[PDB]
Image: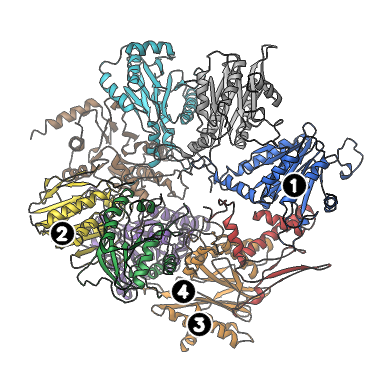
Chain colours: A cyan, B orange, C purple, D green, E blue, F red, G brown, I yellow
Amino acid sequence: SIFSPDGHIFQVEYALEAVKRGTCAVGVKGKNCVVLGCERKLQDTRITPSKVSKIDSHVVLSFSGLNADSRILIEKARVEAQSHRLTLEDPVTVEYLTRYVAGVQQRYTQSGGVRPFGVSTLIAGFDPRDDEPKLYQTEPSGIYSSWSAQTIGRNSKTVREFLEKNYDRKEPPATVEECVKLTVRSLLEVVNIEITVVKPDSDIVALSSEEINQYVTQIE
Amino acid sequence: MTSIGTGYDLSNSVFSPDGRNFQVEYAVKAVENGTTSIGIKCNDGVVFAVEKLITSKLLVPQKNVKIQVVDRHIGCVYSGLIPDGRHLVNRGREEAASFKKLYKTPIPIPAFADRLGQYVQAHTLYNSVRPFGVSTIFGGVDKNGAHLYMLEPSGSYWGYKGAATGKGRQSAKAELEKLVDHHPEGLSAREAVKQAAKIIYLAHEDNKEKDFELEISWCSLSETNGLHKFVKGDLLQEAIDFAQKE
Amino acid sequence: MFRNNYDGDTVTFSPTGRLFQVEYALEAIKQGSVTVGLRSNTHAVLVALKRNADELSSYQKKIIKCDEHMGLSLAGLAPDARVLSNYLRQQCNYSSLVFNRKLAVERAGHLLCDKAQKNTQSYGGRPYGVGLLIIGYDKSGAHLLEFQPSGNVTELYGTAIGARSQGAKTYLERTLDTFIKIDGNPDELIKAGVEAISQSLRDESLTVDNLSIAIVGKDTPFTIYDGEAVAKYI
Amino acid sequence: MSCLVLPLVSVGNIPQLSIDWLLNSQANEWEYLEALDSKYLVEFVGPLDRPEDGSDSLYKDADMKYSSALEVFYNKKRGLFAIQQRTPLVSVNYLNNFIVEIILPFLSKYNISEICIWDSLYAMVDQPIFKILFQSIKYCSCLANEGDNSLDSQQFLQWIISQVKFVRPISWQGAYGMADARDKFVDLYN
Amino acid sequence: YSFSLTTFSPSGKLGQIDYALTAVKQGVTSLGIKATNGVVIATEKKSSSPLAMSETLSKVSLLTPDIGAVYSGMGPDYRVLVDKSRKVAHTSYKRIYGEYPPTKLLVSEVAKIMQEATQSGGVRPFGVSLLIAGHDEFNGFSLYQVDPSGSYFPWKATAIGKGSVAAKTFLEKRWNDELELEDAIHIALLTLKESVEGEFNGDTIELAIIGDENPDLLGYTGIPTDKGPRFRKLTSQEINDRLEAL
Amino acid sequence: YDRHITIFSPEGRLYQVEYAFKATNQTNINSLAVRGKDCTVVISQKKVPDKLLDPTTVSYIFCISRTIGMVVNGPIPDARNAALRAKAEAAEFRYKYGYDMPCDVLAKRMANLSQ
Amino acid sequence: MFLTRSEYDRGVSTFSPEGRLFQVEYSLEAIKLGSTAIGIATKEGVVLGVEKRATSPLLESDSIEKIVEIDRHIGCAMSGLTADARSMIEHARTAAVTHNLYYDEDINVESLTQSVCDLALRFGEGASGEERLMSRPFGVALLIAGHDADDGYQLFHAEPSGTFYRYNAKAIGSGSEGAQAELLNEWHSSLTLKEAELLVLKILKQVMEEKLDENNAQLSCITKQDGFKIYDNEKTAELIKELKEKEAA
Amino acid sequence: YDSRTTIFSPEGRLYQVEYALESISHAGTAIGIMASDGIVLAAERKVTSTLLEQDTSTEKLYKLNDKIAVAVAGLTADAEILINTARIHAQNYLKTYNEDIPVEILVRRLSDIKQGYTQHGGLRPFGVSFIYAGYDDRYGYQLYTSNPSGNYTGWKAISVGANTSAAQTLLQMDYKDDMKVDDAIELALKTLSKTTDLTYDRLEFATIRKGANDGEVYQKIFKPQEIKDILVKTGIT
Amino acid sequence: LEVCPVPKVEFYSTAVITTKIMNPLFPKNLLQLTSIGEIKTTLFSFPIYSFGKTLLFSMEENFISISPIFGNMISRSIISQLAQFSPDIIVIGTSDKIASMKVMTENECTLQPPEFITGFIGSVLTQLIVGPSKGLKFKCLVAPSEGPNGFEKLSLSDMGSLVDLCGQWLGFEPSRYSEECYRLWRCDSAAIGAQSGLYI
């Protein structure tokens, strides 16, 4: 009912099945930036909710899986970010914010009458007064971890294999443009694409379809 | 009868298509496995007696008392799942105290009977509990005289001249019935005590394999001033000797 | 096969009026290791066999003091034993603070009974799957009680519970006439107890590591002997 | 003449329990004949069951010590074949295999003129459609609820017979556990 | 039981609501007809024993002075809705504005009550459909059906319960947008006469109208601005009168 | 579910209620009530076969209030549950509204609890 | 005599016919799913080591945090469904700091352990009768290591069943069956901290599929004077070098 | 187990949500089309009898405030509950900020309510899909939908209810990125005409457009006869 | 539908046939286990062992992942290949359908109704008693257990009984053998109730 005889938690493992059905999301750390990429009609998309959300001025969250589930986490994260500014008089570190978000997820796997979040997330940005790019991933179980580059959702196994042989920790992409390109490349393996660039001290910018199209075409 | 009500006997408070509650009738089967207990209404009082099975000589004699007092004037004895019996008596003690607190006079026996009854039937209302696995024989003296009652797992109860429940209940009921026939003018409390000992003794032939110990209590206007007392000392031995002679 | 339909919760009678969840709880006790209790008119004694997980581990406590004049031993679910003995500690304590009165052992047994009973009549929880042997010394002398998962508590001269406990229980029946007379002689009552629990050993021996002993009595507060404290009896 | 009764493993196991009533209530007219291949079943080894009335153990071979998952039984008189089946199919997929390789060939052999199929149904595609397509046929379901169907099974068998004294297999005595119920009661609540 | 008992099935249908409708479809026919100067609502009074006095029960109920209702389906569900509907008219409307709610809003409150029974944990939907006839100053006369789902539609005329298919048909033929109340009453009778098996008089028929204000039913004089109630239930006598000269 | 709790069957029926009606005949006794010019009489069979019973404590009639009587057809413990509830309702009614609860009003009230 | 399905193992509050709580035993099983953790106690301190087990080269193994400080004198290692360790760690830290606020002393290690086990019980009735705090047992276990003045260096094993054992050495998680057997042979009362440190790597190298380095393994210790320290990659690699160069024998 | 509304299937699917969506695909079709200077909402009525009081009702389109309307597909009574919370949310925002509520903010809140029912509490989801038509000074004219999953997306044109794929195809065919509100009306009527299983008595119709007298935004819930007169002039007469 | 495929099974003095739960009874060193392979396919494989004059066929069970069709077909192969050499067979396993330790032979069934044996040792015993290649001489040791196949749990008593009887039948000394088995038993999850501290 809760545990299988080999010790898995059913609902949690089923939550992971939700993420797999979700659209591809990836993030990769450059030397002085972090890029986030996501995949996707007759719909208006200037008003439609994007897949990457500012949490505070310097931190973003993206996700893969049950879309509507992600809003609760985004909202909870934004509130905590303000609470942290209010009480510690300093904004969250990316790692702190990741703990918070993952802790929320874990909790929803141990309360009665409550379903786990069918989303995994990428959380990225720069700690206040620090220029080392940060990138974390969280899971429905509440596990979290730091990544040089990572992918979640459908075909993430394909995309991950791409990044393992095209991302070199010894030499991380030295420019925002390289970093974006590698992200766009990683997506074209399984792909309409979103890209959001985060540079230190709150330089958060989402690339328009135009600048993205300049990228994809050259790659092709 | 269909003793097993397949599809309707898996949870309490479910009516079978013939309007039965099988869980309550099953609770009765557990009561029928209990040791024999009886009550005898007498002229100005009531008497209780119970069979106590000596399962091992490791039991310490005269401990493990089964008859319980409620307030100062009511006795209770039950057959079946003994802890269900204590649970019910705990409720009765609160009900009694609560009545005595508002109204000052001790709770009358029929009033006490109905408090237990409603509580017992409340446990046939929901699937989140099970029925009580006891039948309870109880009563005492009030402003209206002696009263004796028996209360079943269904919540059903009535007043009795004599009452028996538990494993040896058929045998006991037969002797209770002879007793009634033989005493149209009434039965003194002392007499009822002795007769009670005899009856428990006869009923014990159903559990004849194991030894037993006899426990007897009473509540009588002339003998205990309408308070519940355990029958002890000479009177007890006198009843034990009498029962044995038969 | 038929039992399978009526044993899902403690809130379901079988067609013969059994509560299988309570009966199953009784079986939990057999998964524990043996413990014995016994008494005379002056003292009451517990003896327990403690288990280890392997040679790197400690042995698990089996005896718990509940007050100066009362304690117990357990066989079965360890957590259950922790819950029920804390409850007893609280009841003893309550009796002392409010009434300046040591809780009678007989009253301790009744309180324990009523608590365990509730778990057997309502949906949501489960019966306690642990057995308790309770010793004490109050105004009416020395006592030994056995607690069952059903809530039922019984006053005995001696008994044994847990795995292979039949041997000790037979030995205690067999030796009954003798041990109940061991008055003013605590070490001798303990020796009887160790002897009894020995009847429950299968190709295993009592050591300073696995043997636990407890005693209470007249002028003798509830005391627990482990380690080198048990050597004189081995 | 010849007729085989095939019980299905269905709701409340009444077909199987029906078979138990039939074979033990008629302990004299009945005989163990042979096993069938339990390849597609959860395979089973047990003792030999024998009727609750001290009568004869249906297994006339005084050297055979064990029973099996799948057993045919034979009525010397009324010319009837009865299968008792202890266990269900090792998977829902091998139902087709089981009918083809085990039921059909047994039907060819022995020259059964008619097979009767016992089934149970429950409040909430049904196996015989699987079975039928793999062909005189009698029978199918009955309306049931688990559990303790010691009495539902009799009424079923009482119902089919049209168209005696009832004995249980001695196995039924342990259907609430091997442990004595009187001993449990006295331990727990005395 | 802290979970919905009405849930979606794979076809997307909600079974308990459908089964609720089935109960409604099984009920005694009732109908409503909207005229230019009034509305009529009617039903049959099947007495489930001749020893029963059907006058002591009322299938047509006043909700406000200007609003009334009738039903098909489970009577006790209806009775209870009537109690709730009267209260919500005071608690959510009259106590705030000092005015009775207009028909469509009162229909809307009852709809909410019914919707809630199809979603809240531990409950079955109501097994009734209501027809509700009202008047209000800004909308004039109206007529609504509420279903077990909480859906409501406005009608010029309709029927519900057992004989509703034929009744809706009869009403389609006879209805036009110039009926005066008296026409609508007459047509309602002819309509109910098909559905009626058995007796057919002023004693087996219940009938009410929402029409003109009745100052004679006010109960007091002196406030000239005070409107009489528009709701009136027809007597046995009044109904027979029309029946003879049918 | 629909054979066990009060939810609709596909025929729009409530089985547990239907079965509840069956329960009412289990005591195997009949009652009748008749009205006079100025009185109401209720009568019910009384079957006390067990001679150990006190027949004076066997009753399916109850004095609900000074003016209201009730007779019940069905098992005594459900009977006494209702009797207690009606008595309480009737007392509360007199306290809150300042007059004796009418019989039809008590009946409706209990009907509603039942629904 | 027929084979029918058994619902003995579905509810957490359900006994099997022989008195087992199967849902609880399944949570004990869950530890198998975790990566290896190993604790070794000596008269000079307790060593706690873990297998990191990065699931991809892109994982920054530095953020794999399977050993944490509870207080200056107590650290712990986790294995299993590690997200469940969140509460336990939090509760432990609060227990230790609260004990010091209230009593002006360090919490005894066994107490701390007992305290974590009490929290673990909170899928059901609390040790003091509290009502349930969570809807399932945790699926993680802990090795708790420390020092106190009463019982010196201690190592405890806290199970999600809310029970515990004290050990001289103990291995949990995947591969622990063999790891524990090695510990049975190799452990002795006179082990130095250095030896204990090396024995941990040695047993890890054995059980770990991947080749042992300072990025897939982490050491740490508690000493009475320096308290709890997690070792860094530098120090651990040195220790690994010394292990290789010692297995010249 | 698919009776239970807040538990995952073994494929990480939420059954009750999916079945609620099935129910909606059988409801009366609703279209929404955004023009450069206005929005159009249209709903074909599920229920038809000649005795139905077609005027004085409008039971598929609802004003949420002066600037925002919705079109419903699903249980109308389910809808009413959520419509009422929305009207309240819009009024609270007006009370707190003394500004009209931004369309997306009202939409997100209802989507959050729907989402809630999918993650906790054991109650069935609402069987409704909404098309939101609104105007605000931040984003101008907007169109959104929400469904029992608690998801919401913005559209230039969209449909919900029965025959949705047939409708979407036509709209994909004849939608110009910058049309005029009078053409979007025509397109809407045509598209409902090509999927009807079509008269005025079976239609509800609304618009939100610049009043032209002047500079302000207007919500018109078309009357029955208005629907007639617009049904002929576009040659569906 | 139609007929489904069935696992193709591709293939001394004493043969021991058992499951993976009984691994503690065979201390790899103490009796020096060697190995040979054994494969099957469907449209899994497990090693054979020797020590060194006696074979050991130990099947891996898993309620969750391994269908019993595999063990059915495996039993079918092992018993047929074995019958044409007439070795003395030992079967060791567990049952949740038995109330005590069982020792059985080809001519003595100590089961009492309604006790019985499934699934793999059940398959094995079916082959040895029924169907082709019947008649082989075997002794069968069965301990009570609970839990799904591949997750069995046993009492410490019954683990003890298994060790005595099995060491004795194998003719080892009841010292080094007992000691080496108990070590392996305590590391196994079969005894997890005792090792966890759950039951004391």
User: Circle 2 marks a residue in which chain?
Assistant: I
Position of I87 with respect to C61 (left or right) is left
| Residue A189 placement (x, y as % from top left) | 32, 21
User: Vertical placement of C31 versus C40: above or below?
Assistant: above
For marks 3 and 2, give the one nearer the viewer: 2
| Residue G141 placement (x, y as % from top left) | 32, 42
Residue that numbered label 2 is attached to: I133
Q: CA distance from mark 1 to mark 4?
A: 71 Å
For marks 1 and 2, give the one nearer the viewer: 1
Amino acid beneath label 4: Thr
What residue is shown at x 45% (from left), y 70% (from top)? Answer: B64
Q: Are marks 4 and 3 in contact (CB under 8 Å)?
A: no
Amino acid beneath label 3: Ile
User: Circle 4 marks a residue in which chain?
Assistant: B
Task: Name the quarter where the N terminus of chain G is drawn.
Answer: bottom left
For marks 1 and 4, give the one nearer the viewer: 1
Q: Are marks 1 and 3 in contact (CB under 8 Å)?
A: no
| Residue F7 placement (x, y as % from top left) | 57, 51
For marks 1 and 3, give the one nearer the viewer: 1
Q: Does the image show residue C204?
A: no
- Give the secondary structure at mark 3: helix
Name of the residue lying farthest toward the right = E222
Q: Are marks 1 and 2 in contact (CB under 8 Å)?
A: no
Circle 4 crowding by C-alpha within 10 Å: few under 14, some 14–19, many from 20: many
Camera-side residue: A195 or B45? A195
Residue that numbered label 4 is attached to: B35
Residue that numbered label 1 is attached to: E191
Query: Earlier along the polypeptide chain: callout 4 or callout 3?
Result: 4
Circle 1 crowding by C-alpha within 10 Å: few under 14, some 14–19, many from 20: many
| Residue C21 placement (x, y as % from top left) | 41, 59
Rendered image: mark on residue B199:
3
Amino acid beneath label 2: Ser
